[PDB]
Image (cartoon, grey):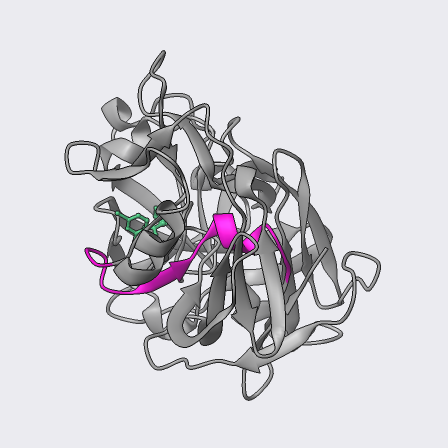
Amino acid sequence: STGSATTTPIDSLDDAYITPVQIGTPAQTLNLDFDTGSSDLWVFSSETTASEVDGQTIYTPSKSTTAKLLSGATWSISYGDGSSSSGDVYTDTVSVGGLTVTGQAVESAKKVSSSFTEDSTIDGLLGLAFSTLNTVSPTQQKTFFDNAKASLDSPVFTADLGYHAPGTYNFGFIDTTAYTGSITYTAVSTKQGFWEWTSTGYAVGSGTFKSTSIDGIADTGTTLLYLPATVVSAYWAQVSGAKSSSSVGGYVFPCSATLPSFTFGVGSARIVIPGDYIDFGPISTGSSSCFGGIQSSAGIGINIFGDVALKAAFVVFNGATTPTLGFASK
Ligand SMILES: O[C@@H]1CNC[C@H]1n1cc(COc2cncc(Br)c2)nn1
């Protein structure tokens, strides 16, 4: 089997991407944040505290004839960006663009933190990291990709995120018309439960490529590109007037600047992030100071190839017995 679904930026800054997902019988369609950095499928629901719902589409398990409460199972997640959610668990049928999984764990939110409430465009998350990170207790549950994997034509899914434009998540096949050149594959460590790999280095604009190992994760759920302080300083030094602002919490730059590109290495291959992918607009409405899309990972403790980097590539998440990661230009 295969599946294919369009993914859409939630706003003009590509802060996140939503993909429609069918849950239950009859189908309840929710727009979920496909997240290769976490491993829980959780949704706003009829059980979510009313004051914490503000525009989201909710899943109502009592109206799904295939929904079954998973007795005694709860979940609770604390994300690296400080957000959180928790609730109970149902099993139900879940479909993504023609691909169907029965008995998927659908984690129903009773509580969500303010950042989720304030974002009316995201109805929940669909985790695509490794199932060892799933938070359901006392019995851990499997991700949608894990449940579907054996039935797929190939045990793979691909992320093709657009810059200010629609994109595609494919399951079970590689669309060879969706990229240029060849796909370069690179080793993955699953020891932290992430799609964790080692970049071979970087370049700023037309500058010389710096060969240096950068261990990080491919995370569609993170907006920005988080890299070591030495690398991020080298990038923003090429933007006149850019500086790290302690009050804003990162590098900012004059909105009138033309940003240089940023290149990262995948083996001997090179992925080029155009300069305007790194512009995240005024720090506050009406300001002429703009927020940078490349930031230091020093506070986070891990390097994150988030949407800023991944949307410059066609990205293969290869879930074979030994998983690997593939990158192509597009
Ligand atoms: O789908 C998850 C919940 N919200 C977005 C995703 N997520 C990613 C992380 C990783 O850590 C950080 C990422 N970006 C900024 C900071 Br400050 C920390 N935590 N949450």
Direction from residue 325 to residue 15 in the image, left or right? left
Asked whether residue 45 is in view, the answer is no
Residue 321 occupies which quadrant of the picture?
Answer: bottom right
Residue 11 appears in view: yes
Q: Position of residue 269 (x, y in %)?
A: 63, 72
Left or right, residue 305 beside residue 27: left
Residue placed most toward the observer, 158 or 69? 158
Q: Quadrant of the C terminus?
A: bottom right
Q: Is residue 123 above or below residue 12?
A: below
Q: Looking at the image, which residue is at 60% across and 44% down? A: 22
Residue 142 horizontal/vertical position (percent): 44, 69
Q: Which residues are magenta?
A: 298-314
Query: Which residue is at 24% across, 23% downward?
Result: 51
Number of numbered discs visible in the structure rendering: 0
Residue farthest to the top?
A: 286
Q: Quadrant of residue 139?
A: bottom left
